[PDB]
Image (cartoon, rainbow over all chains, first blue to last red; front, side, top):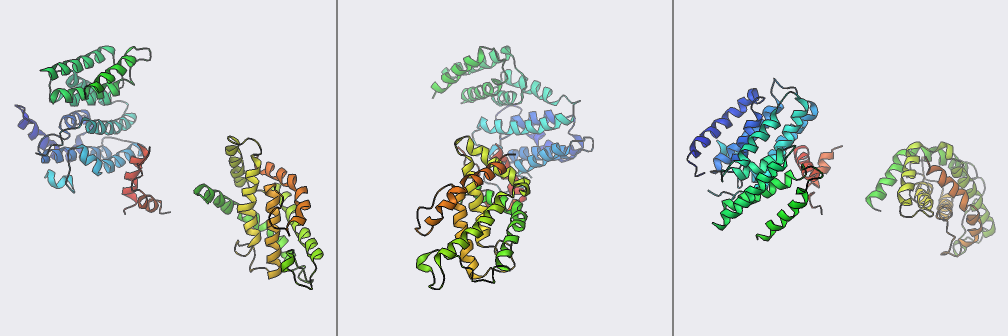
Length: 240
Length: 221
């Protein structure tokens, strides 16, 4: 929210809400990039931008239920219909850092819940179940791979504000992982603990640990790392 | 009476109504239309017996009626509907996992207690007859179902002293019913109900959360 380019992001998020209903024509090329934007924004900033970002997702799911270019199955469409219903629930309002409002729409057109990464984890798996459902029906897409790359780039690169969010998302969405990626994550955990010697660091630690959580089911069956991650968890608990 | 007990009696109800109706109605019409000629009495309680009636004679009357009723049930294996035969066998296997010894006994008792006997005692309310039988028949049917239950439970009479004279009759027909049990045991505003009890479905210990939303979309309309 402090960032030198915050206003430039906030402006484009505003445009993206308005566009998102017209994105009912658009989404098929875009869907990964829009969730990349959701991922960073999901509960950030002043409450109107949060409301906007909830609306952005609602409108995208609705657009995925009706784009005349797409041909999703009754099962996939039903999954999206139930997803709209799910995103309309008070649970999802709290995830998006919306509290004390009847309707997100009204506010869309600070009391930061100091952002809980577990909320982003929840959103991201729900958006993943939306994307996965669609990707079964569209075999010719690259959406999850592009989202994986986009999230991966931001997860690994040093940026204190975004990097935690990205790590969480990368972990949630990924379908494969390498020991070199795990090395980068645990190196990020270590560097974040060095920064604690010197709040942001803690959120990065939490993110890396959530990432390790989602990533560890992916790791190869004979990898030492499964056993190693038990001690990573122990060390994390020790932090208090 | 628990929910699973309600489920079992419902399956007997909706699948065996035509089975009980066509099995018991002929014997009942033979007991009413015929044998109303004589002063048929099944009163076997001595303290309740009229001075004109005879105990020895009424005891025979009960056993004769109980005999042909019991014979018609045991011989009705070839007319047992398949949906129940699946219910009793499903009930047979699940109890056998914890009580493999004499697990067939639990099937036959619940079979007689919750399905056969209630329709025998109250044929009118069960939809088998057009009106209630005469009062003397109602007393005999109630006493007959007590005997038939003792046979199904494989237990002698030990409480009422006036039912002990029939212990010889029930001891002989133990395994005849046991063979019949071994035979049959071997091969909506739902959203209104959902939302009314939807509150706090997630008290457990993913699908319960998912289900709360479908209940809130469908039920609240």
